[PDB]
Image (cartoon, rainbow, N blue to C red):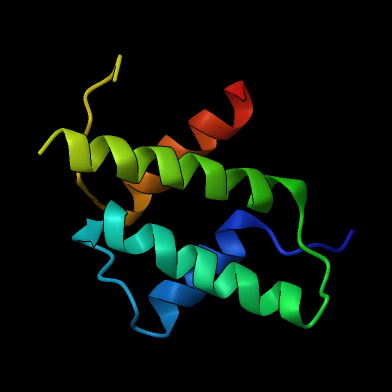
Length: 94
């Protein structure tokens, strides 16, 4: 296409040992995602719309996590495959 996708940013956070794939803190993960998203945009690299929309979703998922330990089972800690499904489900219904 070729654009930075939401998975690209999440995998590089995992691969560089910045998050634990088995216990992800959605509150701590959200700003790490935004940090990396700001890095790509500083270099003016192509970042997809889904990667931009995923930031808004992660901000909501971290706000509800802080308010609850809604209209869903609000979790604070995710696994990587669970967060991937949770984020992609929110991306496609957005």
